[PDB]
Image (cartoon, rainbow, N blue to C red; front, side, top):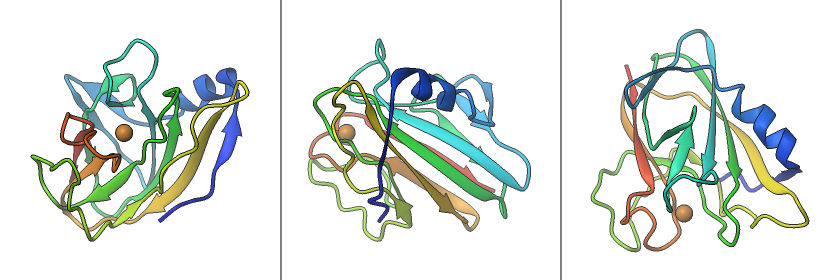
Length: 153
Ligand SMILES: [Cu+]
């Protein structure tokens, strides 16, 4: 799993959030092109706890074109918790301690926000067609809704 983290101040976080290359429609974000950029964040201020936000939507379904290189940036903006962003083919409902192995691509637990900064990381993914789920591994978070669906077709 990806366990390399960097630190960003709030203006940087806001700059990164804007680089998500998807197009929104309802609660679905559709990507296109050879290399797509997904920028996900754990609980942006004002959004429900616990949840992921992508392109300013709460836990949206991501539609990725088969064959595309997926560059994912995950930022933890939630004070007090070190959420994770992990892709699995296991489906909901998720248990308190969810069984999601094998994890196809993902992040380890992120550092908690500190000293006016937020931890973030980048990882690459080359999916095969089919449906996946992005989830947080902190006990009880996926069970309470911190997960979204990904359709690679
Ligand atoms: Cu979480």
